[PDB]
Length: 105
Length: 105
View 1 (spheres, one colour):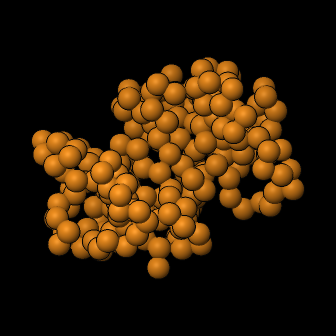
View 2: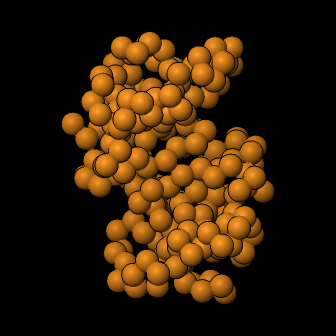
């Protein structure tokens, strides 16, 4: 549960500016009180003409989006997204993101 | 450079709640225009009874503090904290924190 889900910024309305993030960190303190997420967002709001190098995209229910690894921030349990969907198939994205953005694999 | 510095807050006023952060992330985007930081804070205002799990305290000239790894958020270069001091000697803290909390090693 507290990990790998497609967590959309608590309030789906948040998506206007911020739609989601992904639970990826404290396996223990994953969603206990907060988690290290890579805030996903609509590629459209940030120009569909985006380059390829950082912040991976997905193809979820709401369509395509982009892991905002350029910011990264813990999204407290309160606002721990209102389960809109789940992108486990993109599990690597969550990792690679971190793994490159946070480590540079 | 953009990493092992004791970045307080472009506006030291923030320190009331949030005084610092520690540039620690992008090896490539290290000083591009942003860095993933562990928002440091005053052990005092944040309870002197802080745990020894992730929250890495510091003892620098400006005084003792604690990298708030409970959140961790990349502060854009602009507002990347007004250089208050520097804690490279705590470089590992910055790493281990990340490395355990963000990777676990």
